[PDB]
Image 1 (cartoon, chains in turn cyan, red):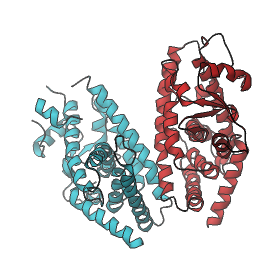
Image 2 (tube, chains in turn purple, red):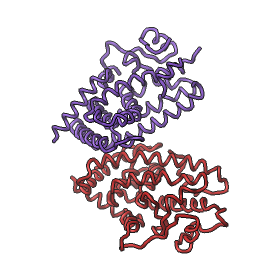
Image 3 (spheres, rainbow over the protein chains, first blue to last red):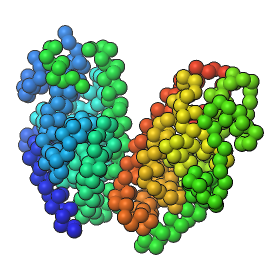
Image 4 (cartoon, rainbow over the protein chains, first blue to last red):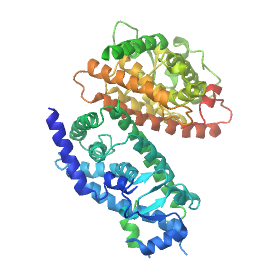
Length: 259
Length: 270
């Protein structure tokens, strides 16, 4: 009954809160009033350099600033992937799946989930970095050299539209689960169970959206159609990655942050 | 009330039958073996193609020297004007979508500019099965294999269409479903360049409501089909792009073959 879907909804939520440090609620308060610890604003080359100094960076140390930002973005991408992999393991039924299938789903669902949540740390003027301690302005990012100047923009554009839906953490938890249980990933050895689980997640999400957003007409449908926006954001990111790789192309560091 | 939603479904289904000669119902009866219709002539090779001309009448593109005005090109020019026809048909359909003609002239053109092809492959599926596709109103049937064996660049145009058609057809949707779905596709508020997005989103929202009702009523047992169908809109975007790159390869592999102006204009695309 309803209960069953809510139980699953509460579960994914609590699981989402444990797996992810910076939630959308927290990020919003930061982006948002809660004035008494405003983030360090990076909008300048000097801002950046004071920032790397003042604020905390576990990924670095004459090498373009542009190239050191893009790399950073990647380093952070790899952290999120572990957070996501742990959360996926809490989705009822995910572990019982063929181990290879689990790997393929994660392998293809990671970018989509990464960008969905990035929107939670974004607004039309910038993004939260250093897991909330900072805020890199959109203008500063768009301001980087040729290939690197337009690498976050497509993401900011998606964020503005996705955020229009005004979803919250409890909404997003079920949503990212649906994305992981995608039966159309290439190489899947057994689609039925995956598809059988996404179906159950889709009902939980639909009910969750309806109880959580009575007035928000057909929100379920609008969210599901934003899933194309992501696919395009993903296809489009691997393309710049192509370009770049014909700019830049440590050996041990390259192995950890492969794709 | 849902009564307003059913009326809307009934209305769109009606305009759909009126705007599209070859429906899915007719397409299937011809493909499966029903007496309600006749058998198609099958084009599975170079010679069936030859024989295809007499029997099957298209006039579109019939002979132009040996396979030199290449069977490939000839088939392509044909598939071009068929596309042009579909566009006109989808255009006529769109005019009946409540509210669509009441929008800014600029947006109407932009909605069709981007919705047309997504609709063409959605509907083209009804004319396909893992083995081939109906051509010339269903009079003919061209094999997936004949089509994949063409000149280096043209043997790649239809495959991702078949690829999509097989999974999409797995949904077992009928004409009453597609009419509302096709409507939704057109009323896409996120199209690039839309001056007014709001009037459009309010119309799609109602259509989404109509489609949502339609599915659960027409497909009682097919769980979450509504979400399953919406997610299909993704495979559609990839069909389009995938194809634009090919049109770009064509535009210069063959500088002697012409592209229909209509199709050309709709192409400063996505």
